[PDB]
Each structure stands twice: as structure tokens, then as C-alpha cells.
Amino acid sequence: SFDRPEIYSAPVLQGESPNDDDNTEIIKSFKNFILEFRLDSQFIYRDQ
Amino acid sequence: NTVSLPRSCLSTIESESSMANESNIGDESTKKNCGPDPYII
Amino acid sequence: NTVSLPRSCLSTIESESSMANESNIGDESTKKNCGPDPYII
Amino acid sequence: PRTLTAQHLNKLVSVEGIVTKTSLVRPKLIRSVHYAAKTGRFHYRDYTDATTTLTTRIPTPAIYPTEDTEGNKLTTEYGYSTFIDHQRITVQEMPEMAPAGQLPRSIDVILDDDLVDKTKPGDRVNVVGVFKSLGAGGMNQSNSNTLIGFKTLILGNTVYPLHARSTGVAARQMLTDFDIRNINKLSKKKDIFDILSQSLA
């Protein structure tokens, strides 16, 4: 009578050079667009 | 976020614990078979 | 006096009574299916 | 064991014989208890099998729980669970009664809880119990094989050791107050040693 084993991870090293058309880079670019894009000197999307 | 409920019980493929293997068998030689579409919401 | 237990529940083919046909359906559209080898001695 | 036939099934019987081999006393799981870390609650579950009840019942094969209803992980409490003992023995017809030049007959017996270690191999034993049949004799599914029949055994509920000559079981008699009075009276005479000596053979 035992319980279930677990699984987990942690980052240590740097993998291969990231390609442009991959989901993580797409997400990063979208996040940058949300948090940085300026119109009339305003952070419209962050504010809204 | 066409999803369907599992067709068969997942407790077999999911070997959660060592005692689960015992629980998955009992009453002599009769194999455990939950039947088709055994899940309820 | 190689007989084997029935493979499927016989209450369907055995239309014993009028109310048995009603009892053979319930909980909306789900069809009744006892499963394979549902009999115990 | 030789004169025990199918016509006695499901009926209370009393068998006599010699124990030929016992089994290792193992614990059986009955109720399991678990603790939830994310909520601080204690859950439990119960288990059962075919041999714990005389009347047939519809199986309820509950699984061993590892998660909470909400998805939280679970921790087991071995000290708060419950276990029960279980032993299996084999009984054979006595050699002072079995047919000579003929192989012997034997029957299995299952003991539980407080009747688990009351005998050892080589004893003469009298067991009173229920002669039962279990499972399905290959009837379910196709099971083209027809040679095998129904499994049978005794749900033993009374066990008695019997003394016999040239056997490892000692003889013991219960002493009554009349016996004690008589023996104590007899002890006080002066020729008791002579009387006892002459009593022999």
C-alpha cells in the first residue's frame, strides 16, 4: 500500500538556439507587444 | 479551452500505485472490466 | 441433465410485462445495456 | 475427507483428519485511511471479498484511492488503517483409518482472525464448518475447457485438536472440585506410593 510517484523539472542549461516560428517565441513576442506598444504616448492595452 | 468522455476506464493504464494493481484484480480469475462508457459526470 | 451462462441480459427479449418495457428505459435518452456476461450464480 | 461428496455442499459438516501443511499467516486489508495535505481532512474507504460472508452478494470492486475528489494528492496512514489475519490449511484422512495401498484424500480449510494459528502440521484435528462452492466452474465466457469443476473448501469456524497414541498432541483433562477433594484426601495416607505403584499394569 503506497502512494503515487511524482514528476517535476527545473531549468539548468541553455538548449538550442530558439527558432522564430515556435510557440514559446510567439508567446514572448505577443507579451512584448501587449506590454510595450505605444500610441499617442500611452500604454493603451496595458491600461485597458 | 469534439471532446468526448473516455471510452474505457483509465485506472488500468494509469498505474497509480502498487496496491492499485492488486485492487484491479479480485474474486479469483475473473478479470476486471468496467464495460463500455463507464463514466458519469 | 457445454451449457454456458447467457452472454447478455435476457430481460429485453423477455417482454414479461407492460411496465417492464418502461422499466427497461430511464434517465433520458441513455439506452439500457447491462454489459457483457452480467450474470452471477 | 474420503466420504465428503457434492451432496453435502452448503451444509454444515464436521470433518476429522490430520493436518498436512499450513500457510504463512498474512494480514488482510479491510479499511484504508488517507490524509489530505491541501485541506487537512482524513478520508477512508472499505473493502470486502467473497469469503467474508455466507450469502452471495453483488461485487463492489472499489479501487485504492490516490487522489482527493478535488484532485489533491493523498497520504496513507498505516497506523490508522485496519488489517486482519488470514491462514489456509489442508486436512487429510488419518493414516489409522485410510485405505491401505490407496492414495489419500484431502480438503482445504480457510481460517481468519482469532482462529489463525491454533494448529501445526502433524496434528490430529476435528474441524466444524460450512462446505461451500465459489466462483463459476468455467461457465462464464466460452471457456472451452470442461475438465475443471467448481472450486470448493470449508469456511472453518470451529477447530479442535485431538490426542492420539504416538502423536505430538498432549492429553489434558479438566479437574473438578470433586477430583481435587479426592486427590487431596488420598495424598494424606502413608502408603500412597505403594498404592500408586501397584496400580500400574
Image: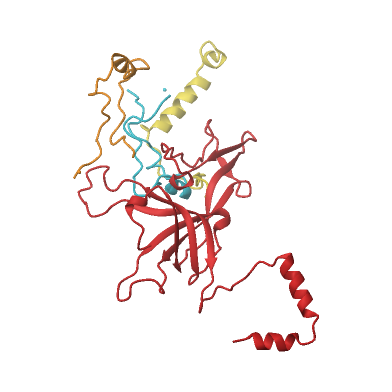
Chain colours: A yellow, B cyan, C orange, D red
User: Where residue D132 sits: x, y (%)?
Assistant: 40, 49
User: Where residue A45 sits: x, y (%)?
Assistant: 52, 15
Question: Is residue D128 or residue C19 the one in the foreground?
Answer: D128
Question: Is residue D70 or residue C5 the one in the foreground?
Answer: C5
Q: Is residue C28 above or below residue B19?
A: above
* Image quarter in which the C terminus of chain A is found: top right
D179 on left or right of A11? right
Identify the residue shown where x is 38% and y is 62%.
D1
D119 on left or right of B41? right
Question: Is residue D70 or residue D160 the one in the foreground?
Answer: D160
D36 on left or right of D175? left
Identify the residue shown where x is 28% and y is 25%.
C11
Q: Is residue B1 above or below residue D46?
A: above
Let me know if residue D26 appears in the view: no
User: Where residue D152 sits: x, y (%)?
Assistant: 37, 53
Let me know if residue D188 appears in the view: yes
